[PDB]
Image (cartoon, rainbow, N blue to C red):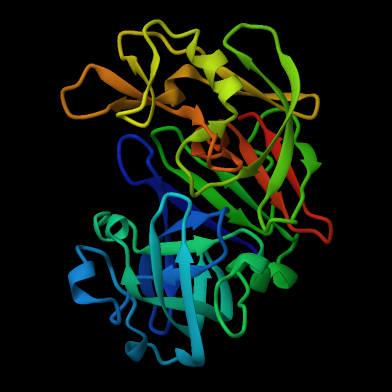
Length: 330
C-alpha cells in the first residue's frame, strides 16, 4: 500500500504545517502537525477541558463505531518548546492520504497547555519519530508509520515541505519526480529515539565549505534550524546589523539586510537553504527588527534540523531494519 497527503503551512511564515487525517467511522477529519521529533498521535477531543479549546476541530470517540477505549492507558508529553498535553487513549481507524491503519492508538487530550489552545489551526500531532519515545503507559504504543510499515510497498515515508507553499508527505514510495539529482543517504542513530544523523559541515553564502561533524535530528515539528553557537555566529556575522538579542530570545536583523544562503552537508552532497527561507519577519507588528531562522542550539542539548532546513530538500525517512535518512535537492 501507499499514501500521499498534502501538507499546508498554518500561516504566512511557515511556522508549522498541517496535514488532514481521517479518524474513526464515519471519518472525522482533523488537521494534524506531522512531527518527526515525537512519537505520539494525540488530538483535541470531546474530552479536552472546555476552557482549553479555542477553534480546534475535536475528535469525538463516542461518535466513532470503530473507537475502543484502551483501558487503563494514559499519556503525558512535554515538548522542547515547553508546551505539553495529556489524557487517555482509544484505538481507532486512522487514514492519511489513502493509507489506512486499523487499531491505531489515538491519544485523546484531557489537558493541553496554552500554546496549543492559542493555535486554532492545529488539531493535534501525529508523531513520526521512533516508537520508543511514545508516552502511553502502561503499554507503549506504536506510531502510525510503525503500524503501517509492514503493509507499505517500501518501508519509508518522505517529507517534501514547501517554502510559503503546500508540500507533500508520502508513505510507502519515493516520488522520483519530486526532486532533482540524486538522493544521498546517511546513517541514523536511533539511540535517543530520533531521526538523528551527522551533517558533514556547512557554508555561509558563497563562502568556502567548512568540514565539521554536526550531529542533529531531522525534525518536521520544529520551525527553525538550531545549530551550535559557533556556526550560528558565523552565519549572522555576514548579515549587516544582525545581533543576538537576549530580550527577544535569539538573533534578529534589519529586514533591509540581505540574507545569505546557508549550505549544509549530507555526506559529500550539499543542501542549499536560500536566504529568504531564513526570514521570519518582524518580532512584533510594525517592528523593523526581523527574527532569524537560524538560531543557537546551546542549552537545547541537541542540534535540530527543523523546517527551515528540511523544506530546502526532499527528505526520505527510511524505516528499513537499519534506518537511514536521504536528502535530495529539489
